[PDB]
Amino acid sequence: MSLAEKIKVLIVDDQVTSRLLLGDALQQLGFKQITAAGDGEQGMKIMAQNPHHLVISDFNMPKMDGLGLLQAVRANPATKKAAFIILTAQGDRALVQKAAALGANNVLAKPFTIEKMKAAIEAVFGALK
Image: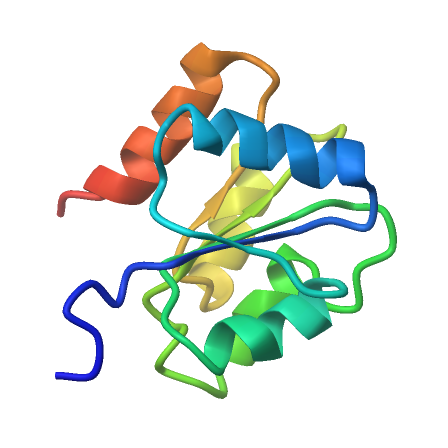
């Protein structure tokens, strides 16, 4: 169609260390494509403007955090298939299901552990039934 792969990873964080970590963790995972722009908002338009299948951001001061992205997806079905990640000192499946049920396509946390991170990604990728 427009993108044989149409599988791009969007990772934008206010802090480099944060965006670097995520990009690093996902890097070793060989995600697909690391796309970062300004912030959730900047990365949202930059991401939407193109193909994407992952939306990970930090909690620094993004104009469009995980939830923010979800809200955007609700306006754009193009990113409605993009799984966003939101790392916070909360990590509650309740919030995940809350947003994930609010309309979000997929909300996963970005743990410092490869086990959790690999699991999250493994889910964001697999997401079978």
